[PDB]
Amino acid sequence: RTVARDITLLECVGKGRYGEVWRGSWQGENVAVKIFSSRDEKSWFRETELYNTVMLRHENILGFIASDMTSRHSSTQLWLITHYHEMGSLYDYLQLTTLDTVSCLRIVLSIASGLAHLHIEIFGGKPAIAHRDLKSKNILVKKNGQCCIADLGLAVMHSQNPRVGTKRYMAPEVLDETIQVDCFDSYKRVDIWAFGLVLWEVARRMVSNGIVEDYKPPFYDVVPNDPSFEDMRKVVCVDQQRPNIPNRWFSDPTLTSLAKLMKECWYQNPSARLTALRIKKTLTKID
Ligand SMILES: COc1cc(-c2cncc(-c3ccc(C4CCN(C)CC4)cc3)c2C)cc(OC)c1OC
Ligand SMILES: COc1cc(-c2cncc(-c3ccc(C4CCN(C)CC4)cc3)c2C)cc(OC)c1OC
Ligand SMILES: COc1cc(-c2cncc(-c3ccc(C4CCN(C)CC4)cc3)c2C)cc(OC)c1OC
C-alpha cells in the first residue's frame, strides 16, 4: 500500500522559542504542524511519550494526529501534527472579540471539561495527567464555540524537561518553592490556579449592561512584560495580590458567580482550591 506522508506547509501561524507552528495540508485536509527548535526537543519527547502511553481523545483536548522524527544531514527534525483550529488561540480571539453570557460560559465550561478529563484517572482508561502550562495561548477556539486545551510538553502522568511553566501563570507554591513535588495532587492544584487566571481573562471580555473590559493578561497592572520569577513571587507570594474584580461584575449574576469561582481557584493553600470536577458542576448551575 501507499503511505502518503507529504504535508504541504502553507503558512506560519506561530513562532517562539519552542519553534514554529504551520497550517498544513494532508490529503486535502488542514492540519497543524509544530516544528520544534533544538532547544525544546524535550517537549516533543514528553508529549510523544504521553500519547504513546494513552491516546487521549476528547472534544476539549487538541486532537493528536502524529509525532514525526526525521533524520537530517546534521540534525534531527521533530514535528507534532494535530488538528487545525482556524480561529486560533483563546488569547488571539479575546483581543478582538467580546462575549455574551452563553458564549462566555460555553468557553469556560469547555476548558474545565478538557481539564477535568486530563486530571481524572480512568481504570481499565487513562492515567491522571496534570498540564503544568495552562494559559490562554495554550487553548484553541473551535467553530462550535467550545475550546480545546493544547501543549502537553510539560505534562505529568500519575496512576493510583528543563522548560518550566509560564511565569505569569505560576501558582504561589511554585514561586515560593514550597510545592510538594512528590505529590501528584500538587500539580492538579497548580493547573487550577492557572485555570482561574484564564477564567478572569475571559470574564473581562463578557459584556454586561453595555460595559466590557479591554483584553489584558493576568497581573498586567503589577508586573512588567516578561516578568521575572522574582517579580511574580513578590506579587503573588509576598504581597498576596490577586487579579482585580471590577465593580460592574456585581451587577451581573453570571459575572458575580464567575468572580466567586475564580476566588476559589486562587487560595494560597493549594488544598483549599476547587477541583476541576467541582468547577464543572458550578458552571452547569450558572444561568
Ligand atoms: C508513517 O508516517 C505517516 C503515516 C501516515 C499514514 C498514511 N497513510 C496511511 C496510514 C495508515 C494507518 C493505519 C494503517 C493500519 C491499517 C490496519 N492494519 C491492521 C494496521 C495498519 C495503515 C496505514 C498512515 C498512518 C500519515 C502521516 O502523516 C499524516 C505519517 O507521517 C507522520
Ligand atoms: C494518522 O492520521 C490519519 C490516518 C488515517 C488512516 C489512513 N489509512 C488507514 C487508516 C486505518 C484503517 C484501518 C484501521 C483499523 C484498525 C483495526 N481494525 C482492523 C479496524 C480499523 C486503522 C487505521 C487510517 C486511520 C486517516 C486520517 O484521516 C482521514 C488520518 O488523520 C489525519
Ligand atoms: C498552542 O499549542 C499548539 C497550537 C496549535 C494550533 C492549532 N490550530 C491552530 C493554531 C493557530 C492557527 C491560527 C492562528 C492565528 C492567530 C492570529 N494571528 C497571529 C494569525 C494566526 C493562531 C493559532 C495553532 C497554533 C498546534 C500545536 O501543535 C501542532 C500546538 O502545540 C501543541
Image (cartoon, rainbow, N blue to C red):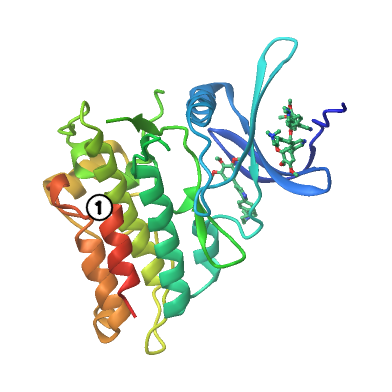
Judge by depth and name the residue closer to the eye, 137 or 223. 137
Label 1 crowding class (10 Å Cα cut-off): few <14, some 14-19, many 20+?
many
Farthest residue in the top direction?
A: 74
**Residue 15 left/right relative to 102:** right
On the rendered image, what quadrant is the C terminus found in? bottom left
Judge by depth and name the residue closer to the eye, 257 or 167. 257
Judge by depth and name the residue closer to the eye, 210 or 7. 7
Say which residue appears at 33% left-offset and 41% top-offset: 167
Farthest residue in the front direction?
A: 124
Please say if 41 is above or below 150.
above
Please state the horizontal and vertical placement of residue 85, each as a whole percent of the image.
63, 54
**Residue 258 left/right relative to 2:** left
Please state the horizontal and vertical placement of residue 13, each as a whole percent of the image.
66, 47
Farthest residue in the right direction?
A: 2
Residue 219 in view here: no
Q: Quadrant of residue 33?
A: top right
Please say if 201 is above or below 38.
below
Residue 124 in view here: yes
Please state the horizontal and vertical placement of residue 53, each as a whole percent of the image.
48, 27
Say which residue appears at 38% left-offset and 84% top-offset: 208
Say which residue appears at 60% left-offset and 56% top-offset: 88
Q: Which residue is mark 1?
A: 275
Residue type indicated by callout 1:
Thr
Q: Quadrant of ligand 2?
A: top right
Say which residue appears at 62% left-offset and 65% top-offset: 143
Q: Secondary structure at mark 1?
A: loop
